[PDB]
Structures are given as C-alpha cells and as structure tokens.
Amino acid sequence: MIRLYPEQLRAQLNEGLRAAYLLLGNDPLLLQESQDAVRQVAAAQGFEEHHTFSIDPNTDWNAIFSLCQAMSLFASRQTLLLLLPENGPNAAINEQLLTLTGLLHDDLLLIVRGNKLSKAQENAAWFTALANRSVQVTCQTPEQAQLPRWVAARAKQLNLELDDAANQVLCYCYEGNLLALAQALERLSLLWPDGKLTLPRVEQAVNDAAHFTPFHWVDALLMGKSKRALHILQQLRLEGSEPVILLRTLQRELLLLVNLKRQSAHTPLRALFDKHRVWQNRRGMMGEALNRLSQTQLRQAVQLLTRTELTLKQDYGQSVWAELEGLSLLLCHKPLADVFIDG
Amino acid sequence: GPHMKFTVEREHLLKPLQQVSGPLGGRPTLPILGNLLLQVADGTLSLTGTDLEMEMVARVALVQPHEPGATTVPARKFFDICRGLPEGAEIAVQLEGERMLVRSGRSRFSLSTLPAADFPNLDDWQSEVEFTLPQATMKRLIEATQFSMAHQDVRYYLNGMLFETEGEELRTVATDGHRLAVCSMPIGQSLPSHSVIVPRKGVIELMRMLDGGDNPLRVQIGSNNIRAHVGDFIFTSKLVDGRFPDYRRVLPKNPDKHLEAGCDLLKQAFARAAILSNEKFRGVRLYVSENQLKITANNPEQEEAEEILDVTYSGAEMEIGFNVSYVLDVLNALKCENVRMMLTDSVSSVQIEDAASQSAAYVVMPMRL
Amino acid sequence: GPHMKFTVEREHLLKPLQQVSGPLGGRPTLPILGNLLLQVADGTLSLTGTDLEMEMVARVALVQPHEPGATTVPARKFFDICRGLPEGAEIAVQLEGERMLVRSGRSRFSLSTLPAADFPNLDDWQSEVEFTLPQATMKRLIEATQFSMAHQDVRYYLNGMLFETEGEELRTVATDGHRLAVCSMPIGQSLPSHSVIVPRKGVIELMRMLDGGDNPLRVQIGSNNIRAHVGDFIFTSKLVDGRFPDYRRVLPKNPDKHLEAGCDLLKQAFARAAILSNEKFRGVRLYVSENQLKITANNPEQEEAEEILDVTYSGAEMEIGFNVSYVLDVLNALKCENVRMMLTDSVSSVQIEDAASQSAAYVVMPMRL
Amino acid sequence: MSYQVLARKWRPQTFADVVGQEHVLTALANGLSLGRIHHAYLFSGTRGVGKTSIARLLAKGLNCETGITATPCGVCDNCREIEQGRFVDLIEIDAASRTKVEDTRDLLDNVQYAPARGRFKVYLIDEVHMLSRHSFNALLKTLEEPPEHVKFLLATTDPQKLPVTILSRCLQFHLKALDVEQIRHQLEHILNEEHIAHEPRALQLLARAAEGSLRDALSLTDQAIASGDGQVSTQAVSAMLGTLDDDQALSLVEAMVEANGERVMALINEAAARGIEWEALLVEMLGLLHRIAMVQLSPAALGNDMAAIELRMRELARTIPPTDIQLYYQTLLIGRKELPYAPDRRMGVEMTLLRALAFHPR
Amino acid sequence: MSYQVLARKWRPQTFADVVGQEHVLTALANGLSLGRIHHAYLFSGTRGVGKTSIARLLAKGLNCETGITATPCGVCDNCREIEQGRFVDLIEIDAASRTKVEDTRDLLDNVQYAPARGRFKVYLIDEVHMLSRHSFNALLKTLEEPPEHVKFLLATTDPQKLPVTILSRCLQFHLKALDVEQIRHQLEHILNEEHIAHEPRALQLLARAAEGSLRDALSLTDQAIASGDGQVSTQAVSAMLGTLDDDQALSLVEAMVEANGERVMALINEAAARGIEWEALLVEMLGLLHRIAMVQLSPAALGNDMAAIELRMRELARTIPPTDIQLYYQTLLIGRKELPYAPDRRMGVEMTLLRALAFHPRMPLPE
DNA sequence: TTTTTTTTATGTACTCGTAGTGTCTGC
DNA sequence: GCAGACACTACGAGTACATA
Ligand SMILES: Nc1ncnc2c1ncn2[C@@H]1O[C@H](COP(=O)(O)OP(=O)(O)O)[C@@H](O)[C@H]1O
Ligand SMILES: Nc1ncnc2c1ncn2[C@@H]1O[C@H](COP(=O)(O)OP(=O)(O)O)[C@@H](O)[C@H]1O
Ligand code: BEF
Ligand code: BEF
Ligand SMILES: [Mg+2]
Ligand SMILES: [Mg+2]
Ligand SMILES: [Zn+2]
Ligand SMILES: [Zn+2]
C-alpha cells in the first residue's frame, strides 16, 4: 500500500482516487482536515452518499447494508466512514472488517479513522487484504521541537505574521493540541484583520488548554525542565488522568535509571545501553540524567515513589498529585524534600 | 378569569378528541405543546393540537348554553376521561381560577391548565393552489406509496412524500435510495403543476384523518405549508426545503423482458422463501427461464430455500437478485390479481406494475449476492 | 441416519405444531435448547418440544409409507415454513446428509438438523394423582386468579400459584402480599388432600392448553412434576417447592360492614378515577355512607378526581384507602352482575366477592392510615 | 412588590453590556460584520461567566431585522421576541434535560424545515456536555453537512467531556474568568443603576469572594441586600462572609505560623460552629503546608489550581524559613496520626495546633 | 394528651421559636419584609440545627393568607396544612428517594402549572446533595430562570458535593451549630412545658453531650426521661452518658500529678465500684489534661459548665509546666492506643497510670 | 520516530437494544 | 380473531462515575 503524509495527501487525491483511504493518527486536526479534503474531492468527482459509521464494540454493525445494494434513485457513488476504537480493532472486529473488505463496489469509497495500529493489528487479515489498493495516511502530532515550523506553515496558510515570540507562546500554550492551535489561529485572524500578530495581542487572545501524555512528563523530569514538568502535572490533573498510569510510567524509567547508575561504575555506557534495550532517541537523555543525579537522589526518589504508591493503594488518599509534584522537585533539579517529602 | 363554559355530548366529542390527540405523547418539546388548546367562540368549539410542525383543528358545534373562552388542557387525560364516561353522558366543563372542572352527573374531575396566550399559534399564510379530491383517491394514493419512504435517511428530504400535481392528475412519489413507489390518479379538473414534499409525520396524519367516509377532501398548498379539510378537521403542516429527485429517469427506459404472475402466488412464494434468508441482509435470487421462475434463498449456516413457479415470460434467460423485504412489501401493497414485472439485466432497475392497470408503478434494484 | 419419508397433511400438522411451539420462544440459553423433535413410530408422529423444565408432546396419525425415526428441527423456521402453504397440501420431509428436505408441490427447502440424542428429556414420576375436569371449568378457575400471582419477586415462590385438593373440591390461590385471590369449586371425585405450587410459566402454558368444550382434561399431579392430557396433546412441567401463607388467615373473619353494588358501574367508576390517580401510587380513598360510595383520587399535579356511586350500604363512614390497579383487575375478572364489598376496619383489609356466588373471593390490603 | 432577582433582570442585551471577555466579543463582531461565520460555535467558560448570555446575544444579532450585524437594533419585533422566551426560529434546547436521543431527534429533524421568520434557524443547545453518545452521533451527522440556513450555538461548562470529533467541527470560544476589578466595576454599575447604597470596601469584599464569576457576585449582592436592611454596609458583608467562610485552612495556618493563640482558638471555634470533618481539615492543612514547602523550592510549584489564594500563599512562602515549615508539617502529621484516638476530634486537633504553636515563638 | 417524641412535637412553628441562627432568621425575615424573594435557597450546616424547619417556616411565610409576611400570622388556613404536612402546594421531595434523573424530569415537566391554592409552589428538596449528577444538570436551567410562581428550597448537610454551577445561582444560607447555652436554655423551656422536674447540672450535661445540634439534644433528653422515672436527674444523666461529672477525673489527675499512687489506685477501685467503662475514664482524663493545656495557653478558656471546678483548674494552670502537660497527654494517648490490647481494660488503665507515674519528670518512682 | 498504559471491591446511574405483554383496531 | 401493530414495560449491557 501507499504510506503517506498529510502534506502530500492533496497530490495523492489529485492524481486519482484509490479504492479506500485509511487515515490514521493520534491528532484530531490533521485527521479532520484529511477527511474533509477526501470528502470534498470525492464530491467533486461524483461521490454524494456519505455515511458516518462508528465501529466501537456496541450494538452498531450493519455497514454491509449500504454496500450490497445499488442506488435506485441515481447512480450516486457512496462514501463509508469507520471510527476505529481507542485501541484499534479486536480479533472479532478484525474478521468483521475482513468480511467488509471481502466485497467492495468500485464506486464505493471507504474511509477509516482511528489511532495508530501496532503490528498486532497491522498483520491482521483485514489490513493485509487492504494492503493492495488502499492508501494509508499517517497524521501525528509534531514534537515540541517540531511545532514552530508547523505553526509557521499554518500562519503562511492564512497569510499571517507572528515573528518568533508569538510562535513560542502559542507552542507552549497549545502544546500537544493542534486542534485548539488551529482554532486559535483562526480566532486571531478574526480578531485582527491586519493579520500582523504580535505578542501584545496573542498574549491575551490565547488559552492554557494543553494536552499531554505521561511520557512527556517523564522526559521533562529527565531533562530537568522544572517548569515544563510542573506544567504537565497540572495539565494532567485538570485532564483527570489516572495517577496510577503516571506512577507506572515514571517507575519504569526510574528503575532503569537506578540499574544504570548501579552498573555505571563498572561498565561503559555504550555496552550498558545495548544490554538494557534502550531506545536510540533516549540514549543522550539517559546520559544526561546519569551524569546529573547520584544514587542518593535516586534512592530518595524511590522511597518517595514507594510512599506515594502505598498511600495510593492503601489509605485511598488524595495527596497523590502534590506528592508527584514533590517527586518532580526531587528528581533531576534540586533535591531537598527533607523528610517533609521524603517519608 | 375566563369562564369558558362547555355543555356537550360524549359522542359529539369522542371522535374529534381521538383525532386531535393522536401525535401528542411522550415528553413534548414544550409543556404547552403537550396540551390541547380548547377555544370556545360564538357557538362553536375549536380543539387545536400541534407539534411545532403541524396543527390539527377540530370544530364542534354547540347548542347548549356556553360562554367564550380559551385554555389549554392535558391531552391524554382529557381523552381518557372523555372515553371513560358512560355512553350518552353529558359533559360540562368550567374553567375556575387556574383549574378546569369536568363534570358528569355523578363525577367531578379537576385538571391542571395553561393559559391560551402562551400557546404557539402557528403562522398563517396564503395558499398558492387549491385542490379537491374524493377521500378514496387520497386513501389509495397514501396506501400505494407511504411504505416506500425513507426512514431516517441522511439526505433529510427523502424522509417524506412528493406530491406532484400536473395537468389534471396527481402523483405521489416515495423513495429510500433503493426503492421507488409512484402512484398517479385522476382528479377530474385541470390543475397548476406543483412539486411539494410532505414530511413523514404529515403523511401519517393525513392517512389517519381520512375518516373513510364520503365527503370531499379540500387541500390548500402554499409556498411552505399544506392544509387539508375533511368535515370539521383542518390539518396544516410545514414542508421540506429539499428538491425531490426526478422519478421519471429511475424507471427502466427500455424494459427488455416482460413477465406476468399471480400476485398472491408470487407473494406467498416470496414469503415462504423469506424464512430461510440471511438475517444479516435478507435477499433471494431469481432464475427466470422459459415460462419458469425459481427462487433461491441462502443463509450462512448453510440453509437453502428453493421455489419453482410457472409464470408467463417473454425472454431468453435471466439471473437477478432481490432484497426479499422490498419485493414482499411491494407485492403486499399491490393488492391486485396479477403482477407484471419488467426486467432489463442483473445491474439495472426492475419495474413492478399491475397486470391490468397502470396507475401505480414501483421500481426496485437488484441486490448483489 | 435413516431416510424419513414422512408425509404429513397440513391440516393435521399446523395446530399441533403451534401447540408444541408455544412454550419455546425468545433467545434460548444455549443452542439446541430451542428446537423440536419429530419422531415417527408405527404410523404415529409425535412432535415434542422442551425448555428443560417443560415438555410438549403432540400425536398425529399417518397413513403414508414411512420409517420409524426421530429427528430434530429448529422450531420457528419449521413453523413458519409449514404455514402459508396452499391448503390441503401434503408435506414430505426426508433426511439426507445431516439435513432435512421438506417438499410441498414444487417447493423444496433444506434445514440444518441435530441428532435426536441431543434432545434432552425431563424427569419421570409415577403414581400421579389423576383428575378429570372440564376445560372451561379450570379455565375460569385459573382466570379468576391469573393476575393475582406476583411476577419476579424474591419472597417465597410467588412466581406461581397454589392448587389445594381437599375432599371433593379443588381450590386455587394466588397472592402478592398485598392482594390475594382464592377460587374453590367442587370437582366430583374422591380426592386426597394435597397442596402444590405450579410456576407462572406453567400457568400460562396451562391456559394455552385449553381448547374446546369437548373431551375433558386429565391432570396428573405429583410433587415435582405436573402433567395435562387434552386429547392427543400431552403437557408436562416442573413444580416449585415451598408453600404459600395460610389463605384462611388472610381472609378477614369479621365482614361486619357490607356493601352491594353493580359490577359494571363500579368498574367504570374505578376506571374513571384511576386516570387522575398517582402514576406510581395508584391509590384512591373511599368514603362509605348509607347507599353511597365516594371515591377520591389525587396526584402530584393535584388534579383531584371525585366520583360517587349508588350502593346498598348501612353503617358509618370508613374512609378506606387502597390501590386502584388491584381493584380494577379484580372487577375485570369478576364479570358478574353484582359485587359485595366487605369492610372490617379503617386499618383492616377489604374483601371482594361475587354477590350471587361464593366460588371466588379476593382480599386487598389498604394503602395508608 | 415583584423585585426581580439581580441574576435575571441584569442579563446583558447588547454586546456593549458584556463585561470583559473582549477576546470573544471582538471576534464575534468581526465575524458577523464580515462574511466569515462558522457553522457551529462552541462556548466555554467557568461557572457563570457569560456563556449563555453571549450565546443569546449572538442569536439576537444573527436574526435582527436590520441584518446580520455586531449590534442588534433592539427595537424590531425579532429583538423584542427573542428578548422574551417566545420565538420560533431560535430554539432553546435544555440539552441537560433532553439528553436521550429520542428527544434530540424530534428537534434535530427541524433543520430540514425552513426558518419561519429570520434568516437563520439558530439552535441554542445549552449544557451540551450532557448528551448521550447516540445523541452526539445524531448531532454530528447533522453538523457534517449542515444546511446553509442553520447555525448551531453550543454552551457548556466542561468542553473536554465532548467527544473529539464533534469538537473538531466547532469554533470554540473559551471565556476567561472575570477579574476582580471588572467584577467590582460591574457591581458598582448594577448597584448605582438601582436604589442600593453601598460602601466601596463592601464591594471589594464581594468581588474578592465572588471567585471571578458575575452570577456568584450578584447572588452574594442580593443576599447582602437582604441581610443588610436595604443598604450594603461593610460590616454586614464581612459578617455574612464570616458565616460563609470556607478557607479556614489558610487563615488558620497564617495564625499558627504567626503564633496568635487567641486567633487559632477563635478560628477553631468558628470551624466548629460549621460542621467540618476534622480529619479533612487537618489533611488539607497538611496539603497547604506541603505546597508551601514546594514553593520554597521553586516559584513555579504553585500552579493554576490556587490562583484565588496565590498572593497570600506566596507571602507565606516568602516570609517563613523552610525549616519551620518542615517542623510544622512533622508535628501536624504526627498529630493527625494520633487524631482519631484523642478525646474528641475537635479536642485532638486543638492540642495538635497547640503543640505546633508552642515551638519557635513563645 | 398522648406522648409523642420531642423532636417532632416541638418543631418550631414560627420565626420567634427558632433559637440561635440569628443571621439566617434576620436575613430571611428582612428579605420577606422588603419583598425581595430569591427563587432558590440553599440551607447548609451540620445535622439538626434547623435547616428543614427553617425552610418549612419560609414556606409558611411565603404562602400565608394575609400576603407575603415575614412573621407567619399565627395559624391561618394556608398554614394549617403546612403544620399538618398535607399542604397542596408545598411539595416535599425526599431527594434521596428520587435521585434518578427520570424523576427530576417529571418534576420539571409540571413546573409551569399554576399553584392550586398558594401563591408559590414551594419545592422543598430535602437532602439536595443526593441527586444524581444528571438530575443536577437537569435542574440547572429551571433554577436559572424559573417561572414567577415557583420557588426552590434546598436543604443539605455538606454543600461541597453539589456542583458549583448550582451553588452559583442560589442563595447560600449557612446555619452554624448552636452554642451550649442555646441548647441548655431551649431544653429548660422544653422540660418546663412538659411539667417535668429537672436538675440544672443534668441539663448542662445534656447540652454538652449533643454537639451543637438540637434534635440530637432532644433525643438524648427523651432517652434520659426514659432512663429516669419520667424525671431528668443528675444521676440518670451521668448513667446514660457514661461521663464522670467534673470531680472524679479531676481527683485522678490531681493525684497523678502529685505522684501519689495510693490515692490513684484507691479511686480506680472506687470507679470500678461505680461500674463505669474504663475507656470513658481515660477519655475524661485526657479531656481534663487538654482543658488544663487550654487554660495555660489562653488565660480565659473555661466555659460555664466547668465553673464548679474552675478554681482547681487554675491551680494546675499555675503549678504544672506545659511540657509536663504535653508529656502526660501523649502518655495517656498511647495508653488509649494500647488499652484494647491489654490483658484487661482495668489492667491496661492501671498500667497506663503507672506508666505516667514512673516517667513523672518531677517525682518519678524510685529505682 | 516509538512503543510504550493501571489497583479493587462495591455500589449507583443512564442510555440504548431487544423481548414479553396488552390491547385495539381495521383487520 | 387475530395477528399485528404498535405501545409499553422490563432487562442486559455498555459505560461513567463515586467511595473507600
Ligand atoms: N459579561 C457579562 N456581563 C454582564 N453580566 C454578566 C456577564 N456574565 C455573567 N453575567 C451575569 O450573570 C448572570 C447569568 O449569566 P449567564 O450568562 O447565564 O452565565 P453562563 O455563562 O454560566 O450561562 C447574568 O444574568 C448576568 O447578570
Ligand atoms: N434552630 C432551632 N430551633 C429550635 N429547634 C430546633 C432548631 N434546630 C433543630 N431543632 C429541633 O430539631 C428538630 C428537627 O430539626 P430539623 O430542622 O429537622 O434539623 P435538620 O436541619 O437536620 O433537618 C426540630 O423539631 C426542633 O425541635
Ligand atoms: F449558566 Be452557566 F454555564 F453557569
Ligand atoms: F435534616 Be437533619 F440532618 F436531621
Ligand atoms: Mg449557562
Ligand atoms: Mg431534614
Ligand atoms: Zn432588531
Ligand atoms: Zn399563616
């Protein structure tokens, strides 16, 4: 199949529509834009029957009704949309979609939307059946270092100027949330018809609505970005993420840090990273952490995390969030927490 | 407060209440919308029931002492009390304070009310065309095409019926993206051509309010509403802004093959084959051979149904598919002696008509198995 | 297995098939559970169905050639395919390759089957006490108390009703803890003393069993199994242990306060009063004066409902408050010409009886003090 | 006679009567005056800050007889009609009451009908974060290809509860919580537009205790007028707030750090006059001390949760050495550990505070 | 005639008979006098301090025959049913019994129908903190702009459970727990109206026993009347409460700080002869130690209910160091921690007293 | 790029799908 | 007479959330 990027989706649809489009990714904005572009171009090329059909395991499975039957009124080409689950299809859904792709009209267009699918769902019979004709487009959130270029491109799309301070402010405020970023760019365009966005305007026209995942918090702690770490913890508190997920995501990397610091005094880091199965993007990260924090801070952090987990699963307390902030302070940065936040 | 005196018979009141309290039910959009507007004026009574898209007004004559007034009453409660009184009982209704007292000789009921001022009086308008048709004609028009309307289609203009008045005759069209039902009937007078879409609830109400009698039905169709009069019932409804697609091009322009069969025989053969059809999507396959029709139905647990019937046929050979529900519905609604089928190929539409009449036509698509 | 070759006339098949397919229905707990077994031995075909706590057996005679054998078919599909066939048409069923071919004229259908050994049977019990009673007799015997039993409650085994056999008389009781119904009647046989609880589903099936005023029904009662014979129809079911409270103690022993009224008038008055009663607490209060019964009903929206009826009473005012659904149900069941109310105290329960017959009686507890 | 509540009669009717929140009013004005109007606006805010009022004002502006303008005339029959509850084209749907898809279908099928009076049939769906999943699917199907004659106005308190796909098709205006100065200014205008005498300190207290919402401020103003014998005096508002104070934690920890035994006694007595679980009070006091010790380490520790008590907290963080905070946390923790076994929970928390007070000063 | 529970016989029937809660009564009466009637009231506070009673009194004031009167003019026709609880228009909603949203929807559907007789259809929603979140959200809008002829009175124990968007649009009246003197005076009035003899110390103990409520105080008084022969006597109150009055435990603490074990054990034996719970003795002694600490820190901290021993209090306030008070309190607190695990509760209390004696920082036991 | 994801025991609602029952009508 | 046609009521499940 064709694997494609959101920028080149316009060219791919322009050269010719394929049997089915699999638009996948974690962000809402790029998925929505790609789906809108596909729908508009299909309507230009003669697709009028548009169906939105959620896949989620429930009492909703009758998509076959819309494909086996030719349209009596007009020879109107149809478009079917599927909203994959938050974790992808299961085995039953895998085989059901395999049956769905077992028969498809040439005039029927298939749209599937969902999060990224690992190899477990990639090697399923449904995807392998789709592997010939369908075009899959990946839409992923640019990283915090990649956001400014994307914001500059979006500003050029709307004929806007932001200099650099406004770009940094927008990236910080709407980090990991491209939907709100595009909506805010539209809002700024509406606010000032001049289009010359500057700090004394974007400062008050912006929100704090941000999105995050525990990996961002763990990496912020590893680099020692104190303000970013506390910002992520506050945003996750507002979002209502499960504290246990944060606990486990930190615990994995903290156990890795403890073991690597234990082994550092005898073995070079090049062999240790290979033996411990560390990702290539994190090596330098780990290096910095190992060269920054001694085993005393690591043991204090382990004691703190142990107290946090025990008070979470035994006393049913609500002091978890402040305690994780204390751990953030005690991790790479300034270790004080004297008994106060050290058990 | 308003006096609004009532002194009526039960029989003169049961029928209009049953007619006007039809669609009212469940929880309405507004509390007033769930109440009948009872308005007594001059020597007549108006009962108004609305759903923010239609409005049925029933007129009841008064001969007993009465005083003018207007108030809104719960509909289900009033209908149940009217139907629950003994035969021939006199009903007296008096609005006291902010409650309504309904009295019969040995019973007194109190009911909550709402002011008639707050009732959403539907906007008036001017009809762009008049119309007069005997009731039986409208009955046949609705019965021929109501069943084929789209249920809740996304297009939100197939969920209705197309009234096309042209020259002298009237036509009703319905579709669901896979079926088409068209019925043409004469009226006796030349009329201006008009294309109008009536929502499904309007069609249902028009079907219900026919009364099956003999008095003529009056119709006034405006720019965005329709109104119908039968006896003392006046029903108004809004219209759908969409443009109903041309039904004329749907029908097979060149029907290659003709066949004829017994309506009841074919209907029961289809019904019998329908049991062993797949529930995921029910359909059968027609094998049309020399004076022969074979019905084959399959079900994924390896269930097979076979039927052979002797039909009149003019053609070489045909293999086609059909969603058994659609053909069952069209044959059931045909209600004729013999059915004529027009076939072209396995990938084009199929026409269904009466073997001896042409007023009603149906078009259906094969389903690919 | 073998080749069935069972030729069955439709007239001798449709009704017994419906009879045996009665108890089964809905989605079964496990497959095969929803199915029926047809077994032919020496010219007699038996259709048997089960729910593993019930069984239906229907016997029919065969004149055409066959072989003795038993096969299982899904129930609903066979019931729907046998029906709708042309009148008087024979059905030829034949087993090949683990599937059943059914033929009628040129109509062929294939059905998936299961081995006869996969159809479970129910328990066996001997020395069942025998009963010979008319159909309509036991029909109205249960009908007087069919509503009485409580459905889906934990207390005792109220999901059912009690049969008591004493001397020469059969009595039947049901209740819910607030309403109770008894109906006793002499059968005409020397009988022992027994007290059994038949489940609610068994009661419904027993009602379904009754047909015609011809040959009398034969009961076979035991301790954990019940049987009914109606001609060539045999029904079996599983009983329920436990025992209901003493109905004799439930009935008031001091019916000092008497009331005589008309059945239809009181039923209509209660129906009218129930309209404005509380939807959940359908309770009305009763004022009893000399030859006068007044009923008052309220609800959260107020809407007070009052009615007054002429009765035959002499005494003081009682003001008994009780539920309306119960009294409406019992007055529906009575279908008599006159009704006797019997009151003891403002706290005590009330008794309802036929004025001209003592066969059936009812008791209803009051609502509020 | 009929003195209408200040929360209703003072609802704005023109964009000029809306306080602050210029980042939304200006955007809407530019959008309406120009041609760019999106197909569905989603309003967000916090606890009575001007979502429903602004949505109603937008619906008024969209259907004014003078045309689509930033400023509705307020004179034409449409402005008067939408001003009151009754109007045909503007559909006010209490989504929080008609959550079921069965009720939503009966009102989302009206989109196929023409607007009776105005240019646009406007659906004001209030409290949209309450719909059922199937109802959300129906509304999304409507929004996918909305007719050009229908504009959707959605107002809610928690935007994130909405499914992401519906939010992706709505331009979201987030309303900022009103500032103390804006609250005080609008309250002064409201009081002066009526016959209510006042003292500026009383209005300052009202604004600070209003937690940045005009409905809270107006409710408190009506309560103050009621208990103030028709005049808003400082002592009346202060006494009422004392009856309504809930932040016994910060005040009590301020007193305990400053070691005012009499103030601690008075605050414990006040917290006993109000039914307060002593365990909860003590544990959240521990939390406040924890946050103070965190702010000792980095000024960014104090997030956006406690913006209402930022200043005081920052002061308490700045003026106190960390070792005293650690000692106070230790003694409070050990007191809470033994708290359930004390004579009474009030009794035990009292002596725990005495233990913490005996150290450092005195 | 007859003997019904005090908690239901003496429910206030006018704003004059509501003791304490001066702020809420004043605000309600003043607002009714001015005619300013908000359309949603929320009475918060601890249990049994009169939120339901005040709400019903507000309903009386709103629906009274003579008009919107701050003081209900005695008993008029529209107030008789309120007193009897069968009123046509005061809709009592046991919200805990109607938490489902499919019942608040039914409540909201009929809100617009005019009141049958009263000026307002006062919806008294008892325990508003128990409605399900969907029902809350349902009643949001009907609270924001209710019809002119309906009022909502919401009573609950803890407002924090309610969503803040409901706390916004309703008046918040908070009822503080009543003082000891208020409870004692009201109890004196009640026992006088019942023609029942009583002892002042007994009623002071009743006031102290109930934590600032009144219905709890009335319940405990009724239990006292049951325990006595229809009389509230000091001995009966001491028996029912399990307390030590204010003398025996003071003798214990005085002997313990005097390091005289003989008198300590003698009084322990006497208290055993008194047939009293041992943990009660420990908790009373701990409370006395805490009172000593309080008077040492705050010079004027003793209430009137301890005046009978106040002098001796000051003695310990001038004789024992604060450090020793803390030592004794913590020693006896660990004694309380350990008592349920000692071989015998009497044995454990003896060991705790001997432990406080052995670690006496002034007169420790000789080695 | 990259794959990565957690305590639970118990209880309380809410909303939709689908069966079981009643009844009521034009069949 | 009879399905059959709703019409309605109940129940299971999928899901959200609360408390401890
Ligand atoms: N921007 C504002 N200007 C004036 N009054 C306001 C404003 N915002 C809120 N209010 C006051 O609060 C009351 C309720 O406001 P509302 O707009 O309903 O808040 P919500 O956003 O929570 O629906 C209004 O009657 C008005 O008095
Ligand atoms: N302020 C008060 N004045 C007089 N009696 C009170 C007061 N508060 C409570 N009571 C007593 O308590 C009984 C019940 O009080 P109630 O108002 O139900 O408390 P709650 O707030 O817990 O519902 C009343 O009958 C009354 O005797
Ligand atoms: F009406 Be708001 F959202 F409090
Ligand atoms: F309403 Be209270 F808590 F008794
Ligand atoms: Mg709002
Ligand atoms: Mg109460
Ligand atoms: Zn205008
Ligand atoms: Zn009065």
Image (cartoon, coloured by chain):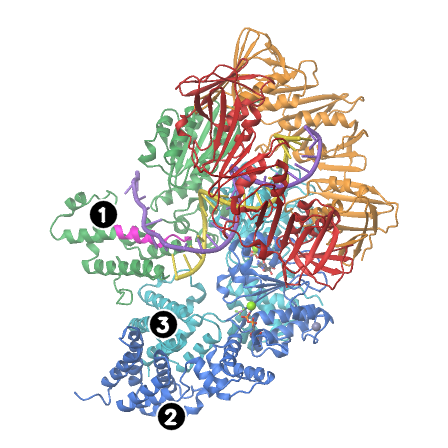
Chain colours: A green, B orange, C red, D cyan, E blue, F purple, G yellow
* Magenta segment, prevailing SS (helix, strand or loop): helix
Chain of the residue under label 2: E
Which quadrant of the structure image shows residue D118? top right
Quadrant of the displayed image that contains ligand 6: bottom right
In the image, is residue B235 part of the stretch drawn in magenta?
A: no
The magenta region covers: A239-252
Instruction: Measure the alpha-carbon separation of dots 1 and 3.
Output: 51 Å
| A266 vs E328: above or below | above
Image mark for residue D340: 3
- Please report the residue visible at 31 percent of the width from the left and 35 percent of the height from the top: A119
Residue C68 in the image: state x and y as whole percent.
44, 20
Which quadrant of the structure image shows residue C15? top right
Labels 1 and 2 in the same subunit = no
Using a 10 Å C-alpha cutoff, classify the residue at mark 2 as few (fewer than 14 neighbours), some (14 to 19) or many (20 or more).
few
Image mark for residue A284: 1
Q: Residue furthest left?
A: A266
Under mark 1, the amino acid is Gly
Using a 10 Å C-alpha cutoff, classify the residue at mark 3 as few (fewer than 14 neighbours), some (14 to 19) or many (20 or more).
some
Determine whether label 2 and label 3 are within 8 Å by CB.
no
| G15 vs E34: above or below | above
User: Quarter holding the N terminus of chain A?
Assistant: top left
| E270 vs D220: above or below | below
Chain of the residue under label 1: A
Residue A61 in the image: state x and y as whole percent.
47, 33
Using a 10 Å C-alpha cutoff, classify the residue at mark 1 as few (fewer than 14 neighbours), some (14 to 19) or many (20 or more).
few
Residue G8 in the image: state x and y as whole percent.
61, 44
**Residue D179 visible to the viewer:** yes
For disc 2, the marked residue is E312
C254 lies left or right of E314: right
Under mark 3, the amino acid is Pro
